[PDB]
Amino acid sequence: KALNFGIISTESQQNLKPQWTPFLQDMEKKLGVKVNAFFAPDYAGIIQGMRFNKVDIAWYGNLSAMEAVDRANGQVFAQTVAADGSPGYWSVLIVNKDSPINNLNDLLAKRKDLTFGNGDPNSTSGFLVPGYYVFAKNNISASDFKRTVNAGHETNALAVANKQVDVATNNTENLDKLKTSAPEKLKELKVIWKSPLIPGDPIVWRKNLSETTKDKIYDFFMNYGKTPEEKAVLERLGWAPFRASSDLQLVPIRQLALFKEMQSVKDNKGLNEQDKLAKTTAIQAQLDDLDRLNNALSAMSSVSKAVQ
Amino acid sequence: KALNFGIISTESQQNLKPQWTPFLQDMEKKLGVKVNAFFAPDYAGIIQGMRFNKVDIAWYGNLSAMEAVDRANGQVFAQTVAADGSPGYWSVLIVNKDSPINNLNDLLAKRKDLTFGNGDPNSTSGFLVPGYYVFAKNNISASDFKRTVNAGHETNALAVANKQVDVATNNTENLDKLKTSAPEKLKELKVIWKSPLIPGDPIVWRKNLSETTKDKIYDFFMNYGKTPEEKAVLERLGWAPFRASSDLQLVPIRQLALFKEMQSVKDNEQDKLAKTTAIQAQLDDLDRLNNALSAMSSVSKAVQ
Image (cartoon, rainbow over all chains, first blue to last red; front, side, top):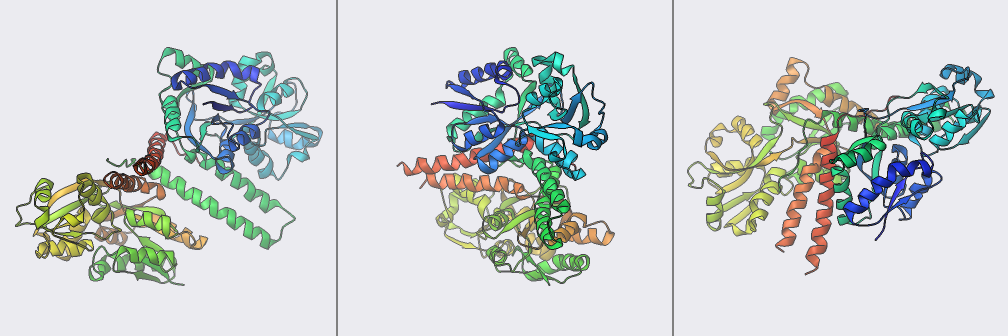
């Protein structure tokens, strides 16, 4: 039977395939089962594919993993690891190198004359992270810009390269990826803002997979990258071997989704003091649970593993 | 409004109070609301109290907390830490000093001639742990002993010291407690079996407690034991400052309950395989979860 592997629409498929085709082939081989590469116009397409069973395993950014866990039966089992040792990556805003915009203050000031390349609604670095640190903390929305459009990281970055949009979201991984796909364009870009650290991308399966199939998949990801051959496959992906993971790694993305809601609620002029208080306290409760869980994780000295 | 603080029937109230009273008073003080101790004749009493909102915060063992979580609307928020630096505690089997039984091998041999004090069906060390390693692993149950009776840790210990029963379950912390309550009965005991390590006892609240109250209870537990007088109270409880925790600490007890159920299925056509694979599936998840936990380099916390 077929396995469908979902690959989020970070880049065009022409650019995605040389990174992923050797990976997927190596999976076919080790599992002795066909592995179809699954693509979509947006992240939602990979998500809903999982919801309807056409997608078995997937590389997600954290936010779309979260969405896949709450709405598409997904579950995190591995986490990707940067080749160069970074413990994650960062969201950025980019403008053309010629632009007189140099930082967020400049951007905010001139927002009304500027077109904006927003990210994919399900993108962590493209949408949620600047959505909070750039827009919500500053009480502004994308609609305060001259014009606003949602696109993937490569589209947004080419658009800025070609002076087709004034400013856009992106991230530092995508900028290295562009160094391979379009170095004369990357040439043209300038970072004007960089977010806090975002944790590495999870790899996610659908739970309603067989006990046996999960086991095969998981052994493959945990053991991949020993040979010189597979090391190269990973380097091309910018990764080092995989780490074991769980839904726990989504914690801070959940806290961030809530900070933003919190801030949106506080700034909403269309609400009572009373409506606010209902909403904020409901948000506060979830935020406290997550704080206490982070305290528990930090305080763990060992992992009790039961003796059979 | 008063808070109710469940305390499991580890020992008799007479022996618990000098340990717990100074603590619950210090909690009354920090919280500025009355704190009432809640007791029951078995652990089930505490759990069922929580289900019906009669207990707010409890000290439980790992089994009964896991039962409070699945059934009584509970949630772990803190972990007890041994004063002596042990990373947990151990279940044991004890017989009288005078007995010729020295180990499990002897016990199992003479089982039919011996009375057995089993624990409280909700006790990790008194019931689940020997239940697996001693019973299920050897394809026998408490019914293979001459007679079997369920009781708290203290009751079992004194019963073995007073030769009212031949062998019973207990744990290493309860033997330390007994050094205080009845050192002469302690003298009469001998450990003949010791389990794999069990994690420290959790402190659990009911999820529907007000937010404010959770916050103040959390703050108090996290900060306890700075003044000299607070250390003493802890010392008399056999504890060092509390550590932050979460239901995740329940993982190995859930594995253990699953190992056991597995084993009782095996010893019990296609009904077996359907049940064993379903257990194995859950057991696989718990292993992958544990791998995730061990592999966490850092705790990524979102910047407000």
